[PDB]
Amino acid sequence: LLGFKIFGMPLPLYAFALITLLLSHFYNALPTDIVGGFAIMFIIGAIFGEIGKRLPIFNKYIGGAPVMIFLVAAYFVYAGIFTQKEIDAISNVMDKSNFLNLFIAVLITGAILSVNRRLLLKSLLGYIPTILMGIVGASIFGIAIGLVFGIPVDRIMMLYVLPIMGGGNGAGAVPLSEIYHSVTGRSREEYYSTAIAILTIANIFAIVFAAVLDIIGKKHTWLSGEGELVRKASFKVEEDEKTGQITHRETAVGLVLSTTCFLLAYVVAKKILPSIGGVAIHYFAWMVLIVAALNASGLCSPEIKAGAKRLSDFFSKQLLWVLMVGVGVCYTDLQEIINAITFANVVIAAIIVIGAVLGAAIGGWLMGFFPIESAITAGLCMANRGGSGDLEVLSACNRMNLISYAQISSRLGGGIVLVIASIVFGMMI
Amino acid sequence: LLGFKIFGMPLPLYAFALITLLLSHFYNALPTDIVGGFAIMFIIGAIFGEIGKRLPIFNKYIGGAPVMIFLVAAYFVYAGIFTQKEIDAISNVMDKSNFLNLFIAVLITGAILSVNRRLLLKSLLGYIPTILMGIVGASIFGIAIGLVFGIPVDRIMMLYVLPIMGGGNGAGAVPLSEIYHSVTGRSREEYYSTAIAILTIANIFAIVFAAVLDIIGKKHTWLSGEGELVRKASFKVEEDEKTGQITHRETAVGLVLSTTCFLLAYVVAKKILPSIGGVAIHYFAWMVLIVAALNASGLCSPEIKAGAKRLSDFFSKQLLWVLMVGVGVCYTDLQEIINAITFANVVIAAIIVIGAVLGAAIGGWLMGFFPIESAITAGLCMANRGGSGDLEVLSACNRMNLISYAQISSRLGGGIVLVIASIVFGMMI
Ligand SMILES: CCCCCCCCCCCCCCCC(=O)O
C-alpha cells in the first residue's frame, strides 16, 4: 500500500505534506503570497486530481483530474471549508500575480514554437480551412437548434457557440468576457458564468463524442486512418532539419521568449495597433500571430524551439493541477453553474458539438485528411477546453500521437474565435 | 559576430527582445504583474550580467553578474530611467508576489535535501564545528578591530559581524532586519542599509581573499589539498545509492517539498513554537532544521532528492539574474550604500573576513579537513552573499567540486547566524 504514489510522492511523504497543510489551516497561519498559494494548491490539486483520475467513470468520460479538481475546490470555497487566509492567498496568486496569464502565455508559445517551420507552413494551407469549416458548421447547427428551442440567434451567437468553440477558461472565456464588456458594455459576471457552465458541458460531450467516434472508427475501417492525419501517402516527403541536446539554458530561453512575446502582444494590442478597422483584436490573438511570425522568421534555433516545447510540457504536466485549484477558487460559483445545467442548455451544447465534429470531418475530407482524426484534431479539441481536456479527448480516444496537432488547434482556434467574436460583438451590438 | 550568445540567445533574438522592451518603455504600456516583471527582468539581467561577465577586472575580482546587475538596476531606479509602471511591476514581483521567499526556499531545500543522508550525518560531526569556529574567530577579530577603531562592541557585533557572517540579501539581511526590529524595537531600514553595504564590501573582500588563498595554496602544498576537503585516505571506502532516472515529476515533487517545508516552518515559527526558550527563532532557521530532519528521516527517495537538486540548479543558474534585478530595484539604495563605504568600514570588513578565514582554517585542521579547503568552504562562502558569492568564490579559485559544501555552508550557517543574532539581540537589549 505504501508503494502507492500521489503526484509522484510516496504515501508517507504526502502524509507529511497533508499534515503541514492541516496544521496551517487549523492554526490559521499562512503567508498570503505565492509561497502560501503554491503550498495550499499543490497539495489540494495532488490529492483531488489523484482521486478524480482513479474514479472510473469520471476518469473515463467526465474529464478526470482538472474537472474534479476545480469542481471540488469551488465546492470547498462555497462550503466555507477554506479559510479567508487561504482564499486570499489563492486570489493573490492568480489575480495580483496573474499566474493564469503566465501559464497561458507559456502554453501558447510552446504549442506554436514547438512545430518545425516547414511543417507549420505545410499545415497552415489546409489545416486552417478545416478549423474554419468546423467553426462554421458548429455555428450553423447551434443556430438551427437555438431556433428549434426558441433561444434567439443573437443569444446563441453570444453565449453558446463562441465560448464552446473557443479555448478554455484562461484563454477563450475571460478574454471573451473582456471583449464583451468592452464592446457591448454589459456586466461580465453573468456572461462569464453562463459561458463557463456551457463550456464545461461541451467538454463533457466532447470527451464522450470522441469516445463514440473512436468506436465507430473501429467499426468502419475506411474513412479512419489510425494515428495518421493526412491521406496523401502519409506525408511521404518529410525531412527533419536537426535537433541537439537540450540543457536548462534552453528552457530558460523558452521562458524568456514566452514572456517577451506576451509583452509585445500586450503593447501592440493596447497602444500600437488597437484596431485594424472597427474590430478590436485581443492581445492573445496578437501573441499567437507574433509567435507564429517568430517561428516562421527563423530567429529561433532548433535547440531553443525544443527548449520551449519542453518548458510547455513541464508546465502542462505539473502546474496544471495547481492552475485548476486556483481556477476553482477564483472563477467558479456552484449555484449558478448548477442553475445553468438546464436540459435546453445541455442539448444545445450536444448539438453544437455534433456540428463542430461534422464540419471538421467534412472539411478534413475535402482538404485531404482522414475525417475521423480530423474530427478529433479540429472541431474536437476546439469544442473541448484545450490545454486541459485536449489531452483527455486524445486519452479517451486511442490516438495520442496527435498532441502537437491538438495544441496547435487549441491555440489557433483561440486566436480565431476571439477575432470572430470581436467581429460579431461589434456587428450585433 | 551574430553567433555571439547573450543569455543563451543569439544576437538577433536578443535584438528582438530588446526591441520589445524598448517599445514597452517608450509607449508606457506594461502589465503590472508577474509577466511584465519577468519581461523586464530577464532582459535587463541578461544584458547587464553579460556585460559584468565580459568586464575583465570586475568579473575576476570585484563581483560577478549578480553584483553588476543589481548595481546597474539601483542606478536605473536612482536616475529615473525606470518608468513608474516598470518599478510597480518589479516591486509586485518581488514584494506582493514575494518571489524572493520562493527563491530562498528552493535554494535551501535543494542545498540540504540534495546531500546524501549517510554522508550528511557523517559530515555534520566535523563540519558544523568548523562553521562555529569560523564564526567565533570572525566575531573576535571584529571586536578587536572595532576596539581599535573605537566602534562599540555591541554596534560592531550587530552591524558588521552578524550581517557579514550571515547569508545573502534574501536570508541573512532581511531576516536579520526583522529580528532586530522584533527584539530591539528599532527601525528596520537604517539597520538594513548599513547591513547590505557592509555585506557587499565583505563579498568583494572575500572574493579577493579567496584568490589570495588559491595562490598561497599553490605556493605551499601541505595546506592545499588539491580541491579535496577531507584528509582521511581520500575516501578509500565509499558507496552511493543509484539515483535512477530523473523526470519532470521529480522536479515538481521537489517544488512541492520546498513550498511545503517553507509553510511548515512559517507555521511553527509563528504559532506552534515561537520561542524555544527566551530566544525567538526565525522561520528560515526553522526551515533549515525541518529540511535537515526530512533528509534524515529518509522519506524522500533518491529520485526526489535529485529532483530537488535539479530545481536548485535551475533556479540558481537562471533566475538568479532576475532575482538580482528585483533586488537592485527594490532593496538597494545607492545613496546610503555609497555613504557607507569608508576607510573604517572597509578595514573592518577586511579584518572580519580575515578572522573568519583563520577561524575556519583552524577548525578544519583540528577536525581533520584540509586547512585551505576548509577556509574556502567555511568562513569564505559564508561571509559572501549566500547564493551568488559562493559561485563567485569557487570560480575565483580553481575548485568547483566543493559547491555542495559551499551551499550547505551558506544555508546552514545562515540559519545558525540567524539564531545567534537573535540571542545576541536579546543579550544586548
Ligand atoms: C511563478 C513561478 C514560476 C516558476 C517556474 C519554474 C519553472 C521550472 C522549470 C523546470 C523544468 C525544466 C528542468 C527539468 C529538469 C528535470 O526534469 O530533470
Image (tube, coloured by chain):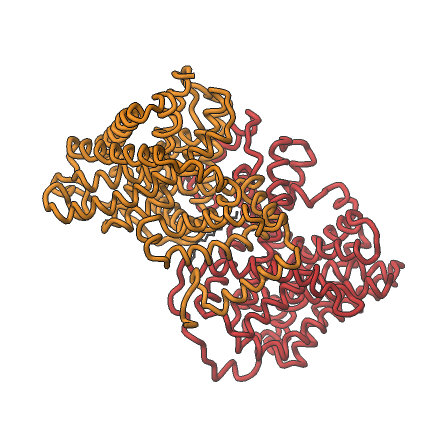
Chain colours: A orange, B red
In the rendered image, the quadrant that contains the C terminus of chain B is: bottom right
**Total label count?**
0
- Percent from the top left, x then y, of residue B359? 72, 72
Comparing A193 with B269, the one in front is: A193
In this picture, residue B397 sits left or right of residue A322 = right
Please provide percent x and percent y for residue B131: 68, 71
Give the residue at x 29% y 38%: A117
Residue B178 vs residue A90, the one in the foreground = A90
Q: Residue at x 31, y 35 (%)?
A: A347
Q: Compared with residue B148, is residue B120 higher up or lower down, i.e. above or below?
A: below
| Residue B402 position in % (x across, y down) | 55, 68
Q: Is residue A311 visible?
A: no
Residue at 46% of width from left, 29% of height from top? A191
Tell me if I can see residue B283 in this picture: yes
Query: Which is nearer the eye, B195 or B229?
Result: B195
> Residue B261 sits in which quadrant?
bottom right
Q: Nearer the viewer, residue B318 or B247?
A: B247
Residue A163 found in image quarter: top left
Q: Residue at x 35, y 43 (%)?
A: A301
Q: Quadrant of the N terminus of chain B?
A: top left
Residue B218: percent from the left, percent from the top?
Answer: 58, 70
Q: Is residue A26 above or below residue A137?
A: below
In the image, residue B26 sits, relative to residue B121, either above or below, namely above
When asked about the image quadrant of residue A406, the answer is top left
- In the figure, is residue A265 to the left or right of B363? left
In the rendered structure, the answer to whether residue B374 lies left or right of residue A346 reads right
